Length: 489
Image (cartoon, rainbow, N blue to C red; front, side, top):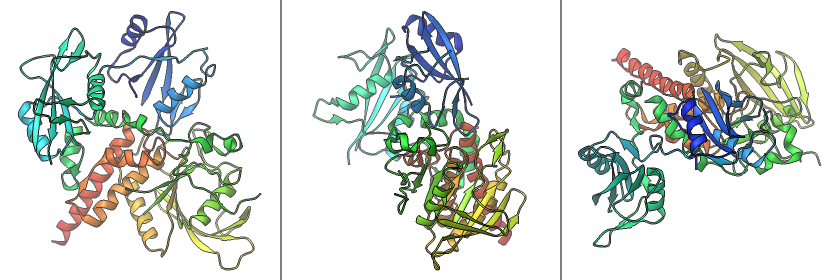
């Protein structure tokens, strides 16, 4: 449940709702990549600023978080942490259905039927606004192996109903109740609400038109964000007191089911803030090294047989340490615990530096392997690059290096927290990989890919600017590939 987030509200409106429909301890989150946490305390409303430039959610005077859901979950369980003491006790639920996957609004009866026939299957449903009855809504459900059933949703005195029974405060409450307790037709047909209609999957060749229609991008990104409370998996290992100083940000943690487990350790030696990212080429999404985790990083690269490292941050950004130097200087050899790293040669490009490293275990003669470090240096401090040409050239080289190495392990990708830039780079790579094998005429789904990657590491792809950049990167790759065909013809 992510009902505490109100996507289309103002400051005074948030103050009015908390003072008339809330109590002391009531709270809601709202957008302004700036966000605000409005909390009622001692009969007054306090506004706490949340900033996200692309790395993490930064609550002013508080902690850093991977998701707004994890931020709320933390302060609801840790009282006294939020001080101006500001208590996060009762979420103020939003009735706005615009961020729901099943809500289509603008659709007509003919448009809803045509879309359910072409894209829908058994249990596929949607909620659209009634055309001839303003204020009312229509629930369209597809049942079969087939038929489309329309159920009228009346709006009477701010409450919603299907013509009888219980009256709901919102369309979300109605949909969820008839999801658990399905409606039965007069001839025994069960109106099961199994899954919403997919309207995000597009043909990679027609990306130009979809980018044009979304130029939309905010509404599609917020719909994806509304699905993050379905990915609140266990992060217990990272929360252990022995692993506290192994995390760059104490609340940005790996999932227990995807975390990289370190073996052959010193007699807790199995933890690293990293996750295996498997598209459903593998990836390891991780944070920027800490002074005390450099040895653990090289232990991971060796054990996982990784031959390519993608660094998408500078060592220092805005006077703050984002990643410590875990590699030696050009032509130098350094020992990092049981691991030995040699920097053979450095090759500089306009947007990145390539470092040819040789990793081996100290005291073992035939464990040496080459590890190629691709260090992207031109990514801006805040936001995303204005042109995706540099990132695409960089990711094409990274891909061809990975493919050229026999039995190469997952590609290690990292920035500062290992979720924003790391998430953006991995998602662009996954989406381009589909086009690389199938061609320009293939199905791609940008929010579905991000959601799948987010189930493997919390908060992968942090901002709407990064979300737009992913679309812009795929569009530029399709254009350059189609231009290459025209030049040959």
